[PDB]
Length: 229
Ligand SMILES: NC(=[NH2+])NCCC[C@H](N)C(=O)O
Image (cartoon, rainbow, N blue to C red; front, side, top):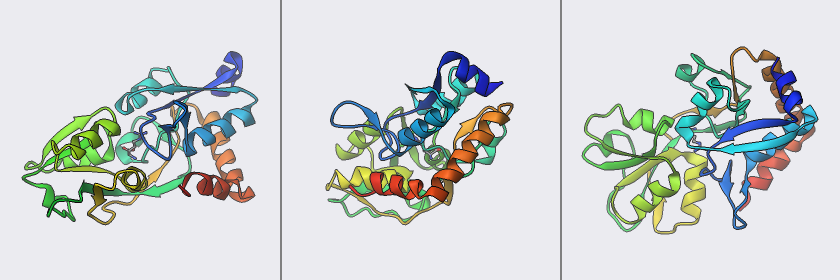
């Protein structure tokens, strides 16, 4: 069983892409930290095992999970019907939606995806933001592995906008006063922890930890920890 494999090796293998503050990011000490890293530590601790974070490209997470290189994905991942075809998700643990970020020193203030037609828009490959902008034939989409590359591209004027999730948009804009979020929230997404569909033992265990975190007040402590910059 899944729990048995974890306990046999002595550590939980968690996949994520650490370019997504405040969920998983590289801090001033060069350490991977964040809200999701803390969720990962709670799950591992409650299993009686150590934690191993496996950092990788975002679009590699699902295939890493299906190919059994990781036990679980905790990486700011939106629950979607398409992804539910191939993995299972925990109870939702956060709400977000896509927003559009542009340079402040420009007249351009897009409010919808249709406002991006005729523009060049940077996205992280494989995300819900990529999926949505990709629907609009007149958007010139530039896809990146890391949001740090997408913001560099935006800041230097090579792209007109970046489309990404609300909370991480706000985290990036807080550090970049040359940027602004021009749109409201364009989707209604929830984050989930992804596990293989056959690993219902692990899934149930993760749901129990989530429910306990909320009941105990520790979830609100974690929110305060990561959303009070
Ligand atoms: N750690 C990350 N880069 N996460 C990107 C998540 C973006 C979006 N919520 C999605 O599931 O597509």
